[PDB]
Length: 344
Ligand SMILES: Cc1cc(Nc2nc(N)nn2C(=O)NC(C)C)ccc1Cl
Image (cartoon, rainbow, N blue to C red; front, side, top):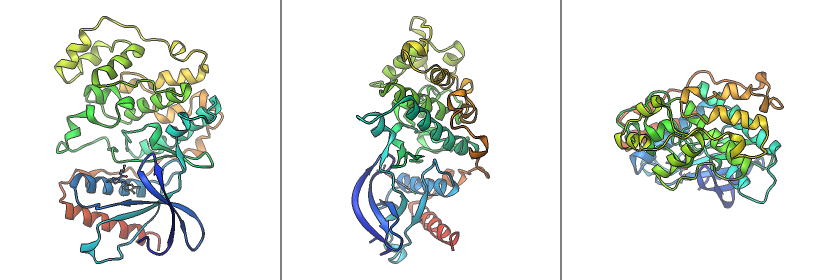
């Protein structure tokens, strides 16, 4: 059941949320995507994640971030409510599908896709939200070339609970190929700078239409980053949590960084200038999303008056709480109610 307000067309694929249904609002004919989260309250970690995503997507109001158009209200008694139905914007493709296809992808495509990504990020980052899992598949693109950041399951603030495993096991946070050196190496510096490494990776991937660091495992991933970036500094090496990784990096002959001009021959000069400001071992050495929008490479689209920040910041306190499956269900049901009490 989809509240009798919608008409289901077909089951489509989604880069950010796996499998969704293309549908239409029966009154207006407006095309939408309907995500079903089956048995949503069965497992603690899944239930916590649904709550996190709902709170994050409700807090944001930005064209480059995926929006909740509607959330279906429980039709059955409370005890029987097991599946959540979320109405999202209908996004036909994603950046993974576009990069890795026979479709055009000129420097102008790259410039415009990076612009939309950084626009959405400047806003997200000012709310003290770190996506922590940016990748081409998570950057939804529609028929009108609108890029929208989706999939906030890995998202956290500047402060995290020690009660969760990823607080210590940072190398398991997100996707290997786009995972920031501070997460790979447990450098105890976890800011929005994490996302700018991932942006750099996506930027490189758009320029060559191939993954920049497609490591086969943990060590191989580090070897790939070090083949381009060179050996990390002694300060980065001293900050490495694990003794085996630290010893492994120290066991290697020194390597100087490879110029980006050698990595991407004949690629646009301003594109490579910006890329080098993102791909740095040191998180604090990286350009912020706001300063990147000021870079000459994005001058074409850059309008400071059309690139908002997000006020107030987003608070992750709800997520640090040890909540039972029932308490999470209660908090999700209260999000549905709030979403509806804020419209009417
Ligand atoms: C759009 C939206 C999506 C979710 N998705 C969600 N929650 C949980 N637990 N899994 N999940 C997935 O999308 N999983 C797939 C990747 C297989 C939750 C809330 C909202 Cl608003």
